[PDB]
Length: 230
Length: 230
Ligand SMILES: Cc1cc2nc3c(=O)[nH]c(=O)nc-3n(C[C@H](O)[C@H](O)[C@H](O)COP(=O)(O)OP(=O)(O)OC[C@H]3O[C@@H](n4cnc5c(N)ncnc54)[C@H](O)[C@@H]3O)c2cc1C
Ligand SMILES: Cc1cc2nc3c(=O)[nH]c(=O)nc-3n(C[C@H](O)[C@H](O)[C@H](O)COP(=O)(O)OP(=O)(O)OC[C@H]3O[C@@H](n4cnc5c(N)ncnc54)[C@H](O)[C@@H]3O)c2cc1C
Ligand SMILES: CC(=O)Nc1ccc2c(c1)[C@@H](CC#N)C(=O)N2C
Ligand SMILES: CC(=O)Nc1ccc2c(c1)[C@@H](CC#N)C(=O)N2C
Ligand SMILES: [Zn+2]
Ligand SMILES: [Zn+2]
Image (tube, rainbow over all chains, first blue to last red; front, side, top):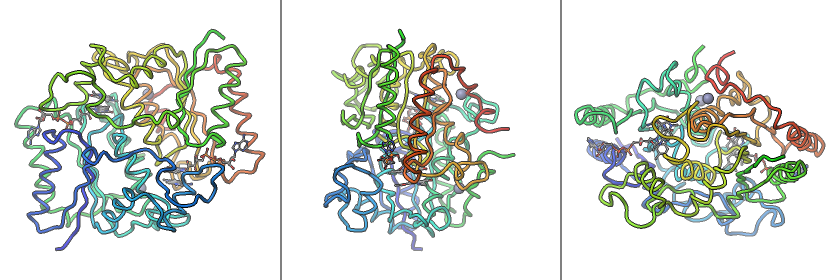
């Protein structure tokens, strides 16, 4: 129908390749009749740092500050900072969450890493127990849409950077799977800066076109073998 | 003695296990006569976000903001924000950089991700020709000292988390090796929260003990084979 999508978007420049990919997601999902929300982290000046400012209530231990303990508890008490609960609400209502970002050091840009650290808290995204396939975000989909400086070939088994999937592990498995998401196959747009005009437009249309049938997709097996082989 | 160490420290609580580890590292390298510097990111309230505030004066293209390019030009024209250049100065001067942090989502806390995104800029950490064996910081040593919530057992090849080396790939290879560091074996203190006090003392001591002979160490071969194969 009928689906609710959250795009968590991490690029500074709306005219970027990232902004284009974000905009065609919105266009295409919107045209399908889906409900769409965008967390534009840079435009929000989203706070990436995990600090005692994230808890507004009496601390469980005010002598020695433990971020994980205090946020678990603030979540249960509903004394978390409001910028964190606003995201949680977006995540809670979403059926699909797409992360749109350029790769920074084989990972997400810090502003997005901060959204992950501060938003996916214990009690909300997972618990002990209640992680991986019993993770709290079960029944939800997640998809990483990454753009790189390096080419497709750099990111091969035997290229300098190794296989692209190697860098996907901490994000797909250690974070998304861990919270219960089914993970859809990543969308990697390699080296747009080097690509020609045509190859770039093909890359944008390929994203557009994949989204046409996104609801029909099966998740990847989010395992050590998918990521590493052998 | 005669060598300079920078410890980049990412934890909110001085009385924490990360604090204790940073403190025995200071005490021990200080005892041996080394020059020691600590960037306490939270105490500094270090800016994690990559933005146009990172370039002072006027941008070489204020129409389309491209962080990589503008930070490359700024580096060469001595026009980076001073928080960035302060950190580069400490790194330039260090013979060993130690990173001391709790594992957040199979990675570094966002605050430290920000340090790496913003400090390790093109022209400073790496450039074309210089990356991997020829990255700009060759001659230097680096070491990840990570603490985990999860046990050693969870972090094996057939455990729920996979092998530790799988999450180390983006940090050690895609970041440290990429900038031309020789990387020392990670120091991983598994699950200090659920260990006895004892075992805890054991892990602190191993770190202290290990730092006595840190200068004698062979760096790891930072290969895909090291991280992924048998
Ligand atoms: C701190 C930092 C760390 C990095 N780490 C890594 C790393 O670890 N590994 C790696 O491989 N790379 C890395 N990079 C490079 C980075 O990932 C790439 O620069 C980024 O993915 C490029 O995406 P972009 O949107 O910024 O491209 P852009 O530069 O914005 O896009 C390139 C070109 O595409 C054009 N374009 C925009 N929209 C369209 C459209 N609709 N149709 C056709 N063309 C369009 C733009 O106008 C531009 O001309 C890093 C960069 C930084 C700044
Ligand atoms: C956002 C977030 C994401 C996380 N992601 C992951 C993840 O992906 N994987 C994972 O495994 N874990 C993860 N964790 C758990 C986290 O890594 C651990 O909680 C953290 O590493 C614990 O280290 P600490 O210094 O904060 O422990 P502390 O709680 O400060 O230390 C444990 C105990 O040691 C005591 N202590 C302090 N100094 C000494 C000393 N000198 N001798 C003996 N005891 C001492 C402390 O008092 C405390 O009782 C995550 C946590 C958070 C908040
Ligand atoms: C400005 C910029 O492109 N930075 C950057 C930083 C780190 C890396 C890269 C680019 C790429 C390659 C390219 N371009 C890479 O593999 N790593 C680790
Ligand atoms: C507060 C806290 O322990 N958070 C946390 C968050 C994420 C993860 C963990 C703990 C560990 C497990 C533990 N402890 C983990 O494997 N991941 C992915
Ligand atoms: Zn998985
Ligand atoms: Zn390597």
